[PDB]
Image (cartoon, coloured by chain):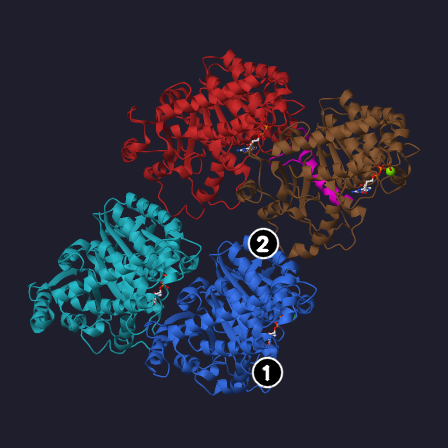
Chain colours: A red, B cyan, C brown, D blue
Amino acid sequence: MREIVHIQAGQCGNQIGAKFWEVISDEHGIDPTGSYHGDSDLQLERINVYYNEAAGNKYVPRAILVDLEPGTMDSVRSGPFGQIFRPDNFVFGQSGAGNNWAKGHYTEGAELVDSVLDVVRKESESCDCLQGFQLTHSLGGGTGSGMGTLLISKIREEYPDRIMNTFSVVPSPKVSDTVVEPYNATLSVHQLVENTDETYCIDNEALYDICFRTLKLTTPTYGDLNHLVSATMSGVTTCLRFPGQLNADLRKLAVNMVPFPRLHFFMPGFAPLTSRGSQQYRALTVPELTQQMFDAKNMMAACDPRHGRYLTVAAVFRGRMSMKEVDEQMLNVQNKNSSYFVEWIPNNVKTAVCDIPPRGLKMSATFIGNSTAIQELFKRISEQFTAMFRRKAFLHWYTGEGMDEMEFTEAESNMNDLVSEYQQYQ
Amino acid sequence: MREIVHIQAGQCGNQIGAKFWEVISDEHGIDPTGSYHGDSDLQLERINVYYNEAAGNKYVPRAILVDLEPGTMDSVRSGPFGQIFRPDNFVFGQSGAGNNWAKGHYTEGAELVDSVLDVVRKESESCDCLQGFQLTHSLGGGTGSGMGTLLISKIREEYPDRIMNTFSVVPSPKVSDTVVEPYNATLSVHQLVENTDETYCIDNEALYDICFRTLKLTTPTYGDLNHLVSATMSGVTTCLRFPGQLNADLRKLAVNMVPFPRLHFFMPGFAPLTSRGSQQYRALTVPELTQQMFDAKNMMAACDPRHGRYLTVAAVFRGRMSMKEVDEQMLNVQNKNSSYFVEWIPNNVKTAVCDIPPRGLKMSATFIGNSTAIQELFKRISEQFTAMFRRKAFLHWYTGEGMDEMEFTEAESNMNDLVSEYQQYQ
Amino acid sequence: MRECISIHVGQAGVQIGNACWELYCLEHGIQPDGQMPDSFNTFFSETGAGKHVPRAVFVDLEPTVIDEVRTGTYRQLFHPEQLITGKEDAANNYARGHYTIGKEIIDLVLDRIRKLADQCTGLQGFLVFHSFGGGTGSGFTSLLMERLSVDYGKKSKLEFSIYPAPQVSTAVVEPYNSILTTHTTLEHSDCAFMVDNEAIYDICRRNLDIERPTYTNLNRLISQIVSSITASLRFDGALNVDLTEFQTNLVPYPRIHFPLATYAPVISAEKAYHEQLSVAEITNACFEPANQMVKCDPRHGKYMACCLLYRGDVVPKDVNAAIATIKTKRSIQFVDWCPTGFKVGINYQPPTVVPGGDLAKVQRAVCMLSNTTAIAEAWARLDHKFDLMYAKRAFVHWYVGEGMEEGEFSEAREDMAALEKDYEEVGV
Amino acid sequence: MRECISIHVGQAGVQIGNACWELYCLEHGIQPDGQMPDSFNTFFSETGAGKHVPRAVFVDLEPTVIDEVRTGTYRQLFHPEQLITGKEDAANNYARGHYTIGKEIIDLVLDRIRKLADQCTGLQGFLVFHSFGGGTGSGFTSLLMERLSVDYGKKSKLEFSIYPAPQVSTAVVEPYNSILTTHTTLEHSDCAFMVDNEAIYDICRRNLDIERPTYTNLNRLISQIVSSITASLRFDGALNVDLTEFQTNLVPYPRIHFPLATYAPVISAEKAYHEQLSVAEITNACFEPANQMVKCDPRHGKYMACCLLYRGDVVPKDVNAAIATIKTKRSIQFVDWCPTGFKVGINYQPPTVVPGGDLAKVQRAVCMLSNTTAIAEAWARLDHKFDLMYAKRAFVHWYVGEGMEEGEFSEAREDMAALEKDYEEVGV
Ligand SMILES: Nc1nc2c(ncn2[C@@H]2O[C@H](COP(=O)(O)OP(=O)(O)OP(=O)(O)O)[C@@H](O)[C@H]2O)c(=O)[nH]1
Ligand SMILES: Nc1nc2c(ncn2[C@@H]2O[C@H](COP(=O)(O)OP(=O)(O)OP(=O)(O)O)[C@@H](O)[C@H]2O)c(=O)[nH]1
Ligand SMILES: Nc1nc2c(ncn2[C@@H]2O[C@H](COP(=O)(O)OP(=O)(O)O)[C@@H](O)[C@H]2O)c(=O)[nH]1
Ligand SMILES: Nc1nc2c(ncn2[C@@H]2O[C@H](COP(=O)(O)OP(=O)(O)O)[C@@H](O)[C@H]2O)c(=O)[nH]1
Ligand SMILES: [Mg+2]
Ligand SMILES: [Mg+2]
């Protein structure tokens, strides 16, 4: 009945995206050829939310893959599950963006964007009732950031009444993977505040921490990091794909969690997460899950939620569970940690429960926090950007692509405004 | 219904602690994997007092293991029963304290203490109704003494209404195992008088004597010594874990035995103790047990109870016994040895009986004496400390870690005060 | 899909190219005849059946050095028309290279380049290998650079340059040439990667235990760096960086386009066995001045941008940790206008090693491209050298003979003074 | 988990290190090639696969002694970069060691130490082996000590020192060197364990029935003591004592940091069979002056702190009993300000014995570290010796030649006078 259209932009976007797709396939019992080999009828009932049926009992992701370089695409196509994707849904350029937002948004991306838009339009027009769009990408690169952002805006123009979701991997506090990261991030944020309905702030640093401290992983891989993100994504759409006792889809969650339009930057979290050794030495009950959820060590954003206050929290539970227990525990946590919840929104917690747990587990949870602590992240980027601009450093790389200084200033202004707004509510 | 949280600090603390845990496991029919293989339903009814149920019919000690060195931890984990412990409950530093109280309390210990506190908090919050805490450690080292003491204080701040119990191995009269022992002991005592509810004074010298003279053990091991301590501990909590005719738990015992807040340093004792040869040549009756209990050779503190007076005695009996006999015998002993009991507390003896005897035996007893003779121990330490301070010997090792002379003086003052108080009552 | 054209200019360039191409062949399993019994396509075109040809042009104004290529082991590897030779050399004279001799062969070389480009579907750009000191490496290269910009423009151009040493130097006129080529190439080059022969010698002696390093050894060492730089294009990695990237991440102002290369670990089979070559350890090695490939004092300068290209058995987290540690270290200082100073590439393929080479086989390597105000010092000495000689007009007549004017020298001087000023000012 | 770095300075240091490392290898089953077919990790790093490398640095200002290491049986055991040699020795001259010759190599050795430390997760500290009398053992060691304190500071530093004998001595300037190194190292060392070659000779002759003990034998004997000291770190025991412990338990005032070593039982296979080597008997042996490793009169001094490290088949109770007995004995006197004078370690592993060694295999051993006012006597004789020679300014010119000033000698004298005064005053 309801449909979700998936977009992947740039290297990061593609790589997370592939993992996500794999996860989804596993969940719905679909193999790398597109054929359903599942058992439970529940797995197929709402398969149309993510998959088009392409005849011969074969299913294909409603997924669009975009990059200014073909290498990523090649890597994807050759990977496990590369064959399930529709060949015509890979839309690639030849040049690349060289970690330049300007190229992604105004130059190379501009040339290619039309084709992708057309593909998206086609996808929408086949599907009976699109709920909306989910875009996976980084804010630190050129493609995912500049071209992805462009795509968002164009999508919104066509479909202003549909929900626009992003899973954005943002620049970490400790270590930077690009020199121009603050610029790319900032510009992306500028467009995101105005054109998305919600943005899930994923931080690689946080993921690494989780892998090391919670998962006890000596040598985490980028794949492993991506897996967590994928899991979170899966958790977020579970009520669209399976039955439940209390169901909340993308719109319900959004309305519960966004009290003012601009404040839609979430810190996602996933629970439970245990080692191979520490699997034995804890019981699988709701309390444990709750504990895991409400903990700085389990947040996928590099921000301490105890340095701000939660405006809203959405908790999405999967498995056969006592609702009473959930209700009690959510209450109890709030009572305990009253100081970390804004006082003028009574009952800060929204709860949803889906009967189908993920594979291999008896019970799972996904957490979405809208915390005023996110401001810290914004502040750090903002300061950096200001510093860089003070010396006009690297600016000719962007102005050379047709961009004007004024745009930068505007972006800065928006960034500062957002943080001010966050502070006000805090 | 009621819960006990166990803490082990430093080498001594860990080593006694492990033994204790083993003993408890044996008693409750739990094997080194955490699974219950017992027979009697009584063994499992109150298993929650010491063990959390971690699903898959597996049980895990509510035990926190702390040390500034990892070697001890490694030794424990590799030992028999090392696998039953929750891996996340081992909290270890990298540096060590080098038998320096200052390091344990203010420097290295300070760095690590937060983590341990957090773990303890977590443990408490899972358990429905904590009775309180039992800490095993020495007063002569740096970790168990300095860090252990620190832990106590922090615990008390959080949980001021819960019972704080210590099993402290104290410096012997004959031979010293460290040069700075008097300092470490003294400082520990200073904190202990103000922050614990009761302290069981264990002396290695006394244990050795017991092993040689009573147990007829040619070559006692530290393990063997620890065993006795473990047994005593087990005896002390028996009424929480099993049924009985007359039951006394930690609070009941404390109120019976501590007439003034500062006078909470007990001389523990355990009966019966026989050789392999002398097992045949005595009958297992209450009188024998009583005799064993009221005897200087059977006390685990290096102090002659006949050099002071008993303020209070708590006797805890295990096995199927005639209460009348017990009552008579306790009366009779008091009548006989009137001069060793304070005259202004009529009926100096408190009695408790638990129906479940320890394994391999028909009948057992645990003795807790609050004797004014303990003052002797304090005096000996005090004199030594004063002598050392007269020459400012080793002081730079402590002052170098940020400690001030004033603290030492304060500690001395408290020590002297305690002994004066003891003398007054005598 | 996306392709890279290599240009080898003069003796030094040609010899470096020989090494590099050999290494490439070894890495992709291409025999010296062009046969192999598909990412290598970025560097090699395919002809007919079972033959692969480098996307390369070799140019020298004299025949001798290239004649060795055309008679040597890899004679069948290169197509004859892409090995271009004149008759008379530039005789360590920029003017002969740029004007008198160079203007006779430049058109031909441009045509070949154009033809190469015709076979490209996604041209990434050009890598030019040349010395600063030789008449062809300087004069011809500047001519070629300018021409490239007109024909192409927007495509990225990268230079690998044998920068002259402070003490050790072969030519007498080398300073003149270096200044002049710098002046003329400045506005035409996007990024130039300097290295120094002295530094490579020292590293060979100290780290590889080689008593007497030969030019071949140096060339081989250079080849490794080149491989590291281009591995992101020639293989698929975890997190990877193309040729278009560098210029944006390493050049904060257009004229300050001289980042420097450092490779780690460079160690023999003796010292390789007795070491755990971890990611942290290799990374740390790169920020200590004795291992770096240009003789210069980074301790006396500040870092502006740093790019780390890891290869082999490497995982992101440990790299991140290493970077954090480096940041923490007070003796490694970054300019205050650059809070994010690291660009990081990670590729799965370990460095492949040439049979009979000086280097041991390692699980991991790193190539750092670092941009530092310490280059100012290097520039200064060169300037000083120029100044002395020009004060007496020593050798000036030769240049004039070949059509150069004295005013050009003045202009060059002025431009270098400007450059040094710029370098100073960025620092503060 | 917790690791220990060994530094071997000069001939004596190097030779001792050779013994010690051999012993370690024997104990952990490490072959001379670094292979073994996990507590040993505190002393050995692990590289790649099936190779283990000592956490050690060997330093000498001349090549000859270390050249034997690099050509000998254990050439593959050590990594080449951790065996550091200059060209010219310190020629029994503190000044050459500390200034003229030492300042050329110190930076290099510091760098290596830093690199070693980089591979440590829980660095316990450093063990430095050196003579007081040699130019490198003195001058270089003092330089190195000072440097260590600046770089590290809070980490513990321990010295093993061949203290010069009263009658037997090799060098002529030995007193000068001993005083000067004492002066300069005093504020930088936490604890220094002296031993004496005369004493070891006598013990070898008397207790082991060896007519003609060689330096090798002495070294071997030393190695055992070292093993005893570090067994608490290299194995797991009943009741055990780390390197951080000693400094707190043996040093009552900062300058009085010279405890002395005694080992028991040291006996051949002849006299081992015809004896029940019980715990009491071995312990008692250690408090009789003929078995002690420094020539000196404890009967004429008082004990201030005593640390007993037992190894092998030993049970606490008997040790305790032995200690009690010792306390009871009127001829073994402890200062009145120290009622608790014993620190006790007990480790499960019996002493391992080198094939072809002088010592028989025993069930139990003990290493006592004792701090005694009797060291004052030793200091006094040395002082007297210094005084005589300086009265005539004998050899003083040599020191001056290498940059030392006469005033330094005076300062050194003054400091030693202070030290002896302090020693006296503690006694009363
Ligand atoms: N690294 C390296 N440097 C070289 C090599 N051959 C020459 N050089 C350096 O190149 C510079 C000399 O320039 P060449 O390339 O020989 O001269 P050319 O480019 O042929 O110019 P002309 O002969 O004057 O036309 C000096 O700095 C040499 O040290 C080589 O094989 N490897
Ligand atoms: N125990 C022991 N002592 C040694 C050994 N070799 C030398 N000594 C002692 O060390 C002192 C002489 O110092 P060396 O170590 O030979 O001199 P060095 O440190 O090399 O100093 P220079 O040669 O002067 O630079 C004398 O007291 C010797 O008795 C040895 O193998 N074992
Ligand atoms: N979580 C995650 N982040 C990635 C991955 N690959 C790259 N990144 C991040 O993406 C940023 C670089 O952008 P990238 O997507 O490679 O550039 P683009 O291809 O031009 O969009 C850096 O912040 C990297 O940390 C990945 O596989 N997973
Ligand atoms: N009863 C008992 N006492 C011990 C044991 N190990 C050490 N001790 C005592 O503890 C003191 C030394 O403290 P230790 O625990 O080693 O120092 P820490 O590791 O810093 O706490 C001495 O008085 C020893 O006699 C043991 O296993 N059992
Ligand atoms: Mg030439
Ligand atoms: Mg020597």
Q: Position of residue D27 (x, y in %)?
A: 54, 69
Q: Position of residue B366 (x, y in %)?
A: 20, 65
Q: Is residue A74 rendered to the left or right of residue B344?
A: right
* Label 2: chain letter: D
Query: Can you say whether B347 is above or below C367 in the image?
Result: below
Label 2 residue SS: helix
Query: Can you say whether C211 is above or below D317 in the image?
Result: above
Q: Which residues are magenta?
A: C219-244
Front one among D291 and A369:
D291
In this orientation, does residue B171 appear?
A: no
Let me know if residue C241 is in the magenta part.
yes
Q: State the residue position of label 2.
A: D115
Q: State the residue position of label 1.
A: D213
Tell me whether marks 1 and 2 sit on the same chain. yes
Residue type highlighted by circle 2: Lys
Kindly report the secondary structure that dominates the magenta region of the rendered protein.
Answer: helix
Which residue is at the far right? Answer: C87
Ligand 4 in which quarter: bottom left
Q: Position of residue B8 (x, y in %)?
A: 33, 56
Front one among D44 and C260:
C260
Front one among C126 and B29:
C126
Name the residue: 50% across, 60% down.
Answer: D125
Query: Can you say whether C156 is above or below C356 in the image?
Result: above
